[PDB]
Amino acid sequence: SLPFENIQGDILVGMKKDKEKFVFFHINNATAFKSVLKTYAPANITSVATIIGPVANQPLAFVNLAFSHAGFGALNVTDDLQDTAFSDGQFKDSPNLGDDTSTWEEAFKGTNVDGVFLIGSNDESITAQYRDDLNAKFGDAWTIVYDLDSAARPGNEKGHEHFGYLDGISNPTIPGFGTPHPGQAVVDPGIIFTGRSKDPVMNRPSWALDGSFLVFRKLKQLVPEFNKYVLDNALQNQAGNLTVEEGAELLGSRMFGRWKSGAPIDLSPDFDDPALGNDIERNNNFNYSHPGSDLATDQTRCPFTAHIRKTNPRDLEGQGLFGDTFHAIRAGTPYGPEVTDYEASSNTTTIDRGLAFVEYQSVIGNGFRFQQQAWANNPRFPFSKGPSIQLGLDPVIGQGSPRETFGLDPRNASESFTVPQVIISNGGEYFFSPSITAIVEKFAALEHHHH
Ligand code: HEM
């Protein structure tokens, strides 16, 4: 069993707070920075145990902390983690993601970002308080280079991302941690936590035990553009009696793999079933297999290129073509206000909004990076399908090539959809979230005891 009082809570369970502030910073004075850390971190870095334990022992805001490769250097900590993406930094790595850095937030366009504080609470007043407190204690020892507020959407769209789809449904868990939901992935702890069982870096340093790599991406979303696209390309059933609005929601469900309620189209392909989508016990219990259906050719229930089927090809893994290597935990939060009447009427975005995307994994190259580059951006993934069956890009997040996706029309797998870019990367950075002791014992090391 893992020491959940030593593991940063946002990795495994998520902060699950309505408001999440991301404080990206540069380190100006390592000695003064470590000094603050020595007392701040044991008092404020929120553990898994605190998040899942009694509400009585929870602070007003949860706080997590992660460092970039550049931050390691600024703290005189050797990067011996053996993660090539992490060491490169996301800006250098960005061509491999299909990013055009002309759309990046300026603060990310380099290696100036040394780390990030995650602050989760129920009111932006409290996250601002915790930020102000950090500013007061660090003083001139740091500079906040980017300060991003994210918030869960309001009302019955709480838990949904800005396109309207229920999010945070499918994430892996580990053996012995609570009860897995039907269809939920149960992966070896070393796929999420560095140094734990079946960590693919068998060489992993001891101090890194129970850390994880935090990938951050600011992903801007063009919601009216997306809505106008699916309306303009609305699908039809064989009966031919779908309205344009009904065919548009069908097409959206085919792009994602789920209806907006969360109902997986593999279980409910013809119409939304909001009771299914909302039910934790039903909404993830699928693997794309069906009696009488050829996994190699049948896209009538879910296109091979649907977002969730690109990023978690359950059928390929379930056939044993590979293992649980490529699962990772998402813990991001939507950012920006709701779509305004003007934006909707004009089919045009005027306000920045999107997803403050966070994904945790023991190997960046096996989680986020593989899901993006090897799968979403790969026009010949998934492999093992019929040799003439055209595939193309993930129609939600796929980039790097012409955004052509096949198989979205259930009546004609051959029909191509050229989907406008509705998600624009504003960049981010790769970080490492150490264990809580590692924060104090390594990153805040004030003396020079030899080892
Ligand atoms: C604004 C950007 C994005 C949006 C709106 C979005 C939306 C969604 C939605 C609605 C789901 C289904 C809910 C769920 O299964 O939990 C989902 C699942 C998922 N997404 Fe995304 N996503 C975005 C970016 C990304 C990126 C960049 C990656 C990885 C490179 C990714 C990987 C995944 C994974 C692994 C799942 C779970 C699939 C499964 O286990 O079946 N997403 N996403």
Image (spheres, rainbow, N blue to C red):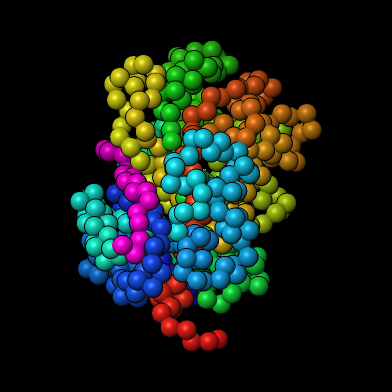
Residue 152 belongs to the span the image colors magenta: yes
**Left or right placement of residue 33 versus residue 284 in this view:** left
Quadrant containing the C terminus is bottom right
Q: Magenta residues: mostly which secondary structure?
A: strand
**Left or right placement of residue 82 versus residue 64 in this view:** right
Q: Residue at x 50, y 45 (%)?
A: 109
Residue 221 belongs to the span the image colors magenta: no
- x and y percent of residue 130 in the render? 25, 59
Q: Which residues are magenta?
A: 140-155
Q: Residue at x 26, y 66 (%)?
A: 137
- x and y percent of residue 429 in the render? 49, 51
Foreground of the two, 116 or 310? 116
- x and y percent of residue 186 in the render? 55, 60
Foreground of the two, 112 or 426? 112
**Left or right placement of residue 108 versus residue 41 in this view:** right
Residue lying furthest right in this view? 387
Q: Residue at x 39, y 56 (%)?
A: 25
- x and y percent of residue 158 in the render? 32, 41
Q: In this picture, is 290 found above or below 138? A: above
